[PDB]
Amino acid sequence: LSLTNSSLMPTLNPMIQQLALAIAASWQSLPLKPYQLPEDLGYVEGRLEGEKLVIENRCYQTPQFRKMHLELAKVGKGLDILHCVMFPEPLYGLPLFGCDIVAGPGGVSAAIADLSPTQSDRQLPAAYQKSLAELGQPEFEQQRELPPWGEIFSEYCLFIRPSNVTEEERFVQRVVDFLQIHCHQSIVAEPLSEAQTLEHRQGQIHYCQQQQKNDKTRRVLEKAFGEAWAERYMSQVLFDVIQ
Ligand SMILES: C=CC1=C(C)C(=O)N/C1=C\C1=NC(=C\c2[nH]c(/C=C3\NC(=O)C(C)=C3C=C)c(C)c2CCC(=O)O)/C(CCC(=O)O)=C1C
C-alpha cells in the first residue's frame, strides 16, 4: 500500500493519485492479510491491434472485508483509470465501497463513488443512512446519469464529470468521508444470523453480476487482451461472484 513502488502512480492523473493515496491511507493500519487474485496476479500488460493496457493490482482482506482491491491502469499514454472495491464479508452485513475514476488528457471524464447496499430492501443500514445524510448534499455542476445496471448503487452514489479543481477536491473529500464512515461502521457492526448472512451474500452476488454489464470496462479490456481474457478478468478478477 505504500504506492512508493508503483510504476504507474507517478504517471497518473492527479485526482487519481490523491484517491489512491487516500484509499491506501484508509487501509494501511487495518488488520490486513494478503488476498491472492487468480494466478496470484499483480502487474499485467497487453496489446492487440491498438494501444497497450497496463494494470497494477493490490489486494487485501480483513475479518470484515472479504476482498479489498485497488487497481490502477493506463491505456496508452492518455487514459488513466482507478478501480477500487471493498467487498464485505457477508457475516457482518456491511455495504460495498466502490470507486471508479477515468481520466484522459482533457481531465477526469468520470468519477464514481458509492457505498452500495446488500440488503434485500436495497437500503443501506440505518447507521450508514444517518452518517451519510450528515455530510450534506454535495454540489456538482456536471452530473451523469447511471446506466440501467447501476440500479445497484445507493442514493448517495456520486457519478460526475468534475468541472474544476474545487470539484475534484470535493469529490476526493467525499470519498475520504465515505471511507471513514465505512471503517468506523465496520468495527461497530458483529454479527448477523445465518438468514441475514445469506441475504447479504445475495446482495453482493447481484452487485457483481450487474457490474459485469459495464461495457465501457469490457471494451477497454477487450481491445488490449480480447474477449476471452476480458470475460475471465471481469468475472474472476474484478467482480467475482461468491458462493
Ligand atoms: C463503484 C462503481 C464502479 C466500479 C467499482 C467499477 O469498476 N466501475 C464503476 C462504475 C462505472 N464505471 C463507468 C465508466 C467507465 N469505466 C471505464 C474503465 C474501467 N473501469 C474499471 O474499473 C476498469 C478496470 C476499467 C478498464 C480497464 C471506462 C473507460 C469508463 C467510461 C468513462 C466515461 O464514460 O467517461 C461507469 C459509467 C458507465 C457508462 O457510462 O455506461 C460507471 C457507472
Image (cartoon, rainbow, N blue to C red):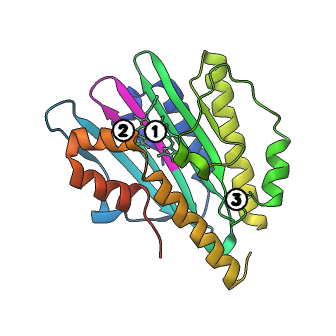
Identify which amino acid the numbered label 1 is placed on. Leu
Main SS category, magenta section: strand
- Specify the farthest residue to the bottom: 194
Instruction: Indicate the position of residue 17 as horizontal and vertical percent values.
Output: 49, 32
Callouts 1 and 2 close, C-beta under 8 Å: yes
**In the image, which residues are magenta?**
73-84
Q: Secondary structure at mark 1?
A: strand
Characterize the local packing of mark 2: few (<14), some (14-19) or many (20 or more) Cα atoms within 10 angstroms. many
Instruction: Indicate the position of residue 192 as horizontal and vertical percent values.
Output: 73, 78
Q: Is residue 58 above or below residue 206?
A: above
Report which residue position mark 3 lands on.
122
- Left or right placement of residue 175 versus residue 17 in this view: right
Report which residue position mark 2 lands on.
73
Residue at coordinates 74% horizontally, 50% vertically from top-left? 181
**The magenta stretch spans residue 78:** yes
Residue at coordinates 50% horizontally, 34% vertically from top-left? 101
Q: Determine the CA span between mark 2 and mark 3.
A: 31 Å
Identify which amino acid the numbered label 3 is placed on. Arg
Identify which amino acid the numbered label 2 is placed on. Ala
- Left or right placement of residue 141 versus residue 44 in this view: right
State which tag comes first along the sequence, 1 or 2.
2
Characterize the local packing of mark 3: few (<14), some (14-19) or many (20 or more) Cα atoms within 10 angstroms. some
Q: Is mark 2 within 8 Å of ligand 1?
A: yes
Q: Nearer the viewer, mark 2 or mark 3?
A: 3
Q: Is mark 1 within 8 Å of ligand 1?
A: yes
Report which residue position mark 1 lands on.
82
State which tag comes first along the sequence, 2 or 3.
2
Q: Is residue 30 above or below residue 46?
A: below
Instruction: Indicate the position of residue 44 as horizontal and vertical percent values.
Output: 26, 47
Residue at coordinates 61% horizontally, 15% vertically from top-left? 164
Q: Secondary structure at mark 3?
A: loop
Residue at coordinates 27% horizontally, 64% vertically from top-left? 39
